[PDB]
Length: 145
Ligand SMILES: Cc1[nH]c(-c2ccccc2)nc1C(=O)O
Image 1: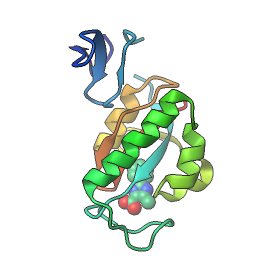
Image 2: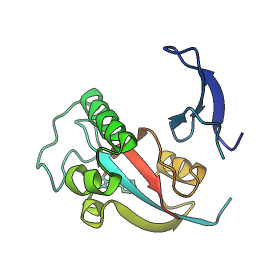
Image 3: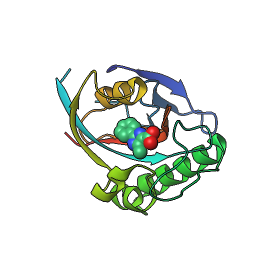
C-alpha cells in the first residue's frame, strides 16, 4: 500500500478498511514523490493555537476537543456530499486563505509546518486528509495538484 497506509478492522462492522497515519484519512476502499503539491485547507483554531485569533473571531476560546468535533462534523458533510470542501473552507476556516476557498497554492517540502507538509505530500491528487494537528490548530487538507 502507498506511504502511510495500513489495513485495519472496523470496530462496528468487522469489515476491513484502510487508515493512513500520516494524513489521518480512512476509507473502505483499498488505496491507489512530486517536488511540489498544491493544497487547500480548512483550519479550526482552538484556545491552545499559537495564535488564538482569526478573521472569524478576535479571541478564539473553543477547546482543542471542541475544535476536533467541528473538524469531524465538516469532514462528515464533505464526505456525504452535503457540503463541499470549498464552501465550508470559505465560511468556517480560521485561516485568511478562507477567502480563496482555502487554496494555499503550490509549495515544496521545507515550507509548511512539518505535520501539514507530510500530510500534503502523502495525499494523492484529489484526496482529502483526516484531522491534521499543528501549532496553528486542526486542519482538513485537500490536495488539488
Ligand atoms: C492564519 C494561519 N494559517 C496557518 C496555516 C498553517 C498551515 C498551512 C497554511 C496556513 N496558520 C495560521 C496561524 O494563525 O497560526
